[PDB]
Amino acid sequence: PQADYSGEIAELYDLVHQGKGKDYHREAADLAALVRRHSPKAASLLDVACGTGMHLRHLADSFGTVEGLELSADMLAIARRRNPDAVLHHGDMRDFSLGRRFSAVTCMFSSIGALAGQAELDAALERFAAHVLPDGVVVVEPWWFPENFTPGYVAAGTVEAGGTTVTRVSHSSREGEATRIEVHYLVAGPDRGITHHEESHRITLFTREQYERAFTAAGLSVEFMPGGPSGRGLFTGLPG
Amino acid sequence: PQADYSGEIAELYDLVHQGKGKDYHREAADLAALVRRHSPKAASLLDVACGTGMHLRHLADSFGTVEGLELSADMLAIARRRNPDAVLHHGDMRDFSLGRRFSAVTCMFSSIGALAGQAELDAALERFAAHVLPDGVVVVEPWWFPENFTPGYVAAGTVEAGGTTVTRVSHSSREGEATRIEVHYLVAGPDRGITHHEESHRITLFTREQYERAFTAAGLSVEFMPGGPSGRGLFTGLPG
Ligand SMILES: Cc1cn([C@H]2C[C@H](O)[C@@H](COP(=O)(O)OP(=O)(O)O[C@H]3O[C@H](C)[C@@H](O)[C@H](N)[C@H]3O)O2)c(=O)[nH]c1=O
Ligand SMILES: Cc1cn([C@H]2C[C@H](O)[C@@H](COP(=O)(O)OP(=O)(O)O[C@H]3O[C@H](C)[C@@H](O)[C@H](N)[C@H]3O)O2)c(=O)[nH]c1=O
Ligand SMILES: Nc1ncnc2c1ncn2[C@@H]1O[C@H](CSCC[C@H](N)C(=O)O)[C@@H](O)[C@H]1O
Ligand SMILES: Nc1ncnc2c1ncn2[C@@H]1O[C@H](CSCC[C@H](N)C(=O)O)[C@@H](O)[C@H]1O
Image (cartoon, rainbow over all chains, first blue to last red; front, side):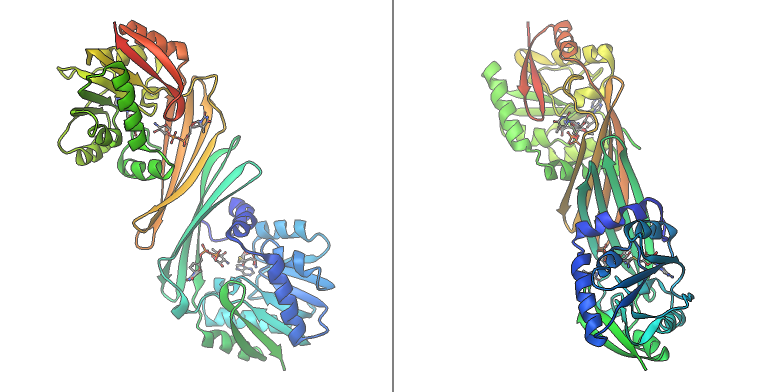
């Protein structure tokens, strides 16, 4: 299985997540209101691990200048197509340097959990702090805390769009201090026939203290609020 | 991919077909009624390619004595558990010889489409007539005809049993004189994780007249009723 968000997996991302019920329009509106709460006059936003650019496409309608960073070229391609007039960088949230700062730096949908341990987490928070304006805000949607993760969780759904049926089923286990989530897809359409795809990801179960440590090492005050877009809450941090 | 109805594919059969809405109770009832129409005092019944023995289990409530014949040892094992007091034979519809005759010889759910070519169809029908009593009836549920099969058809459904989620997705193409149906499964549960399975079959697209000629060569009068249990109609033959 792949772990790199590429190929047909990357192609099926938007369809499966929309079918699961993810509402990027609501999420972007919530996020713009969160940002303006901590930074009333905020005018620009860097979305880190922006994936297919779905958040940016909507954040564009609340913020004058949006920008992305994304490690997977195949995810980035879809995002650039969707956000043709924004700058979207190919790069790595651990070690990136855009030479500018934004009112908000966001990292959504637990993309932070692709990092391996405290050192990587710390390095990414430090980069997020390096790209935020002095009156701005950094927003990170965490993965589950270890005590709130349910090993053995099964998600299964099937959606169809434009002649094609796509079933996605995931199963998750605890693997050391991370979730191993294994995801299988069957994709069937009249002319193309049926194929099976798979991916597999390790998503780190950082504790609240570990996120907090990373924010604080970056010069950011930190606040957690439970709930948020995926039930995992949101951290925000403010420089100074 | 397997073609032989074995292993996990055989274990999944009942759940997926019942999940798809197949009602062997109502089909058994209909079949028993149809049998009696033609042979009012009918007492015994042979189910050829009986698979998991689902029809047999309900036909037992209508006919004094039921028996089956199945090629696949793994399907048959399921059928023997389900029908512990009936005789179920391990054998081939193309050439079996049981030593006795029955009021009804049935062959249901397009099992007859595993045969290729007029010679095999003929052979099977002559065996069915070699096992029917003189006042009894042969019932064969055909596959689609070449004129009414829908190429490109995709089926997808999900069912859950015992904590396990099973998703089955089929694609069907016209592969010459048969339907190629390729079936994929994803099976997931909290304790067992996810597993993928696949089968693929050619199911022969015999014309109406090919079945008619098989029944005729076998000594049976033949009638066709459109619709039937699965949309494909039903043929019935009476020795004579
Ligand atoms: C709702 C719920 C979820 N979970 C965990 C279980 C499983 O690891 C995950 C939900 O699985 P999913 O719905 O198949 O995954 P999701 O759409 O959330 O996407 C997640 O996994 C994919 C692979 C990542 O790209 C994505 N960034 C993640 O959010 O979240 C829990 O532990 N408890 C819960 O109540
Ligand atoms: C609804 C419909 C279906 N079809 C064809 C398309 C496909 O070949 C078949 C439906 O496939 P399915 O629902 O996946 O299959 P089904 O449950 O009927 O099982 C069939 O294929 C399996 C492999 C055999 O063991 C079984 N003996 C067959 O009935 O029927 C048609 O031609 N016209 C139709 O209107
Ligand atoms: N080190 C890294 N730097 C930047 N992006 C990364 C990364 N590791 C993983 N990712 C990206 O993180 C994303 C996780 S999926 C979430 C994508 C998007 N934020 C959304 O909400 O839909 C994928 O696009 C993946 O390629
Ligand atoms: N030559 C042959 N003789 C006997 N059974 C056969 C066969 N070729 C295929 N089969 C059986 O045909 C069945 C098709 S599935 C239909 C099974 C059952 N009649 C039901 O209605 O649910 C499978 O059990 C397969 O193993």
